[PDB]
Length: 53
Image (tube, rainbow, N blue to C red; front, side, top):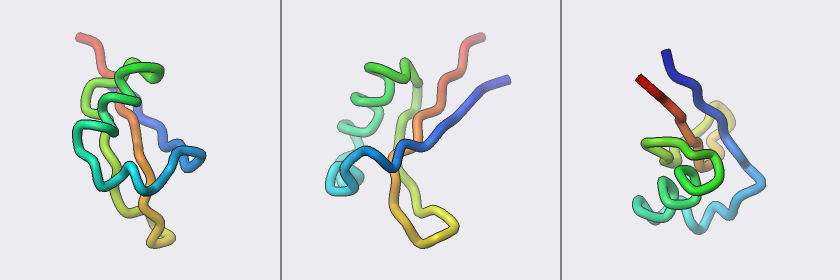
């Protein structure tokens, strides 16, 4: 039972960074594995997933 959300508002240039995504995600979104991935529109965005046992 977890949740996820994408914020296109964020800079795509950061997508290249793997430690930057989760850093900005786990920061505000308090996610756990915040990372970016190609969307259905071939658009690269940073998605944040928040899960709590």
